[PDB]
Image: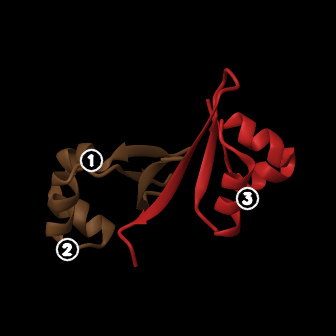
Chain colours: A brown, B red
Amino acid sequence: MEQRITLKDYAMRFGQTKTAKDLGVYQSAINKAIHAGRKIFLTINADGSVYAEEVKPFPS
Amino acid sequence: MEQRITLKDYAMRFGQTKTAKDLGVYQSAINKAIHAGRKIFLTINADGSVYAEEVKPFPSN
């Protein structure tokens, strides 16, 4: 079973820094996304791996 | 606990008619959305309620 958290809550826990290393991005990207208020969720695998996705309702 | 399926896989088990009904949209929307390879997942609630979301990676390659 995996966990799924908001980009924002997670970054609040781990900080832009790890969050960024974890998503493999440049730090400013986390902040911008968050600042923009986009719906991104990170999934954390049972194994520890992390991934991210943005989500939109269907239909719009 | 929820079940979660792709639109496509859902459309095969049940047919395009149930699919649209379930989501309150119409047939064409489904079939279009599907032909176009949109990444949509349907969540099925415990009370049998259905809902969909389009999902994309982040960041984008």
| Residue A50 against residue A58 in the figure, above or below | below
Residue at image position (32%, 66%) is A23
Residue type at tag 3: Asn
Residue type at tag 2: Tyr
Q: Tell me whether the residue at label 2 lies in contact with that at label 1, contact meaning CB atoms closer than 8 angstroms.
A: no
The residue pinned by badge 2 equals: A26
Residue type at tag 1: Tyr
Q: In the structure shown, which secondary structural element does the residue marked by tag 3 occupy?
A: helix
The residue pinned by badge 3 equals: B31
Q: Are marks 2 and 3 on the same chain?
A: no
Please identify, in this view, whether the residue under mark 2 or under mark 3 is nearer the observer.
Answer: 3
Horizontal arrangement in the rendering, residue B26 relative to residue A13 (left or right): right
Chain for numbered disc 1: A
Residue at image position (15%, 59%) is A31
Q: Tell me whether the residue at label 3 lies in contact with that at label 1, contact meaning CB atoms closer than 8 angstroms.
A: no
Chain for numbered disc 2: A
Spot occupied by residue B10 in the image (x, y as percentages of width and height): 76, 49
| Residue A6 against residue A15 in the figure, above or below | above
Nearer-the-camera pick, A4 or B43: B43
Residue at image position (43%, 52%) is A55
